Amino acid sequence: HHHHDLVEDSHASLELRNFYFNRDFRGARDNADEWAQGFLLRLESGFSEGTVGFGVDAIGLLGFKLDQDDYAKLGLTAKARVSNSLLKVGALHFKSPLVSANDTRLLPELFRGALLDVQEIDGLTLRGAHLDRNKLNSSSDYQVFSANRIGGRSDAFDFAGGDYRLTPALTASLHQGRLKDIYRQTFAGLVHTLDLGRSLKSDLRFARASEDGGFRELDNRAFGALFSLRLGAHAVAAGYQRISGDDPYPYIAGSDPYLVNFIQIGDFGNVDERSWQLRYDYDFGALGLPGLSFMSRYVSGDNVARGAANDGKEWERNTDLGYVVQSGPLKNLGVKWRNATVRSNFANDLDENRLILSYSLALW
Ligand SMILES: CCCCCCCCOCCOCCOCCOCCO
């Protein structure tokens, strides 16, 4: 019986987040501070029997400040399954080259709309979405979209894309989408994974955007290259990014851009910006400290447009230090410290600390 299949096969978890966030400006008059507690209840039902299985997911968000992020929200999502392909309608949170929901604050950004994931066929995975609302990570209400830096107003985002495995090691991607009445963007990607005794990942990105509808003329191009070398417990990555045209890298305001040099604070997607990144990771497991992690990265950008000049420059340093409790009562309890420093000649200098204490508990 259907209703009961929904429950019998359902799963659920609760996540607790305690979150401290600090922004210190070099213009101290813009210094923000926040201490908050969040709760996230995730409910995923099973599917009703048949060719097309139906189900329902829910996500409950509660946040309050401790000193916006003072709210409660429940988002429903109807779903429909055939073979291994999935359609969702309602509240959405997913990642893709042209649109990615953010979850780096207390509570996640959500979109409203329809998302369709077609199961991998012959090495090919197709995805598509129609979105019509954005709910910023820090707020409870759904609003229409605008574009980062660029502005505009839009009540529809659409995209379709394919990810194709040319071989087991090489994946090619092509996504096309539109933020209605603001911009159109197309993305092509190539990713090579070399697994030896140790690994090298090569990630190439190219995206072009222009205006849509009656929006002011818009021209942007963004090329990215990221090479990530895994060497035992060590990892080093080098990234290169170049933004071109009259306009900066467009994306839905509030969301995450798919730029290889997008980091804790900056996207390095300013007009004409050229940037390079070095990144290091160490996993302390082999050493005997499973659960301890460290990450450090640096990005330097130049060629940024300042009026008719191109002498804008910036750099940002990030450091992540994190520990997950491995055993005992408090098992799965995780603490993470994210520290960022930014300096530029076209924006304000900033130091930022994020401290996140998180605990996840399976209900069933
Ligand atoms: C948490 C502090 C992060 C600072 C980064 C330190 C850089 C670590 O580089 C060490 C790499 O050294 C390679 C080891 O040299 C090979 C010889 O011995 C290897 C066999 O144990």
Image: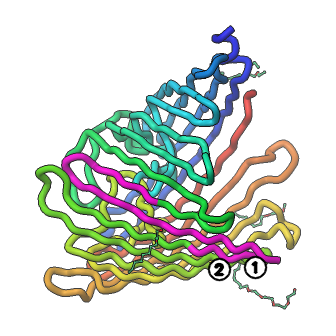
The residue that disc 2 covers is 236
| Residue 265, picture quadrant | bottom left
Question: Residue 185 versus residue 134: which sits nearer the camera?
Answer: 185
Q: Is mark 2 within 8 Å of ligand 1?
A: no
Residue 112: x and y in percent read: 39, 34
Q: What amino acid is at disc 2?
A: Val
Residue 187: x and y in percent read: 40, 62
| Mark 1 nearby-residue class (10 Å; few <14, some 14–19, many ≥20) | few
In this picture, residue 131 sits left or right of residue 9: left
Element under disc 2: strand
Residue 283: x and y in percent read: 76, 70
Question: Residue 344 versus residue 267: which sits nearer the camera?
Answer: 267
Quarter of the image with the N terminus in it: top right
Q: Main secondary structure of the magenta part?
A: strand
Please report contact status of discs 1 and 2: CB closer than 8 Å, yes or no: yes
Q: What amino acid is at disc 1?
A: Leu
Question: Residue 11 versus residue 31: which sits nearer the camera?
Answer: 11
- Farthest residue in the front direction? 122
- Whether residue 295 is in magenta: the answer is no
At a point 39% along the width and 58% down the height, the residue shown is: 32
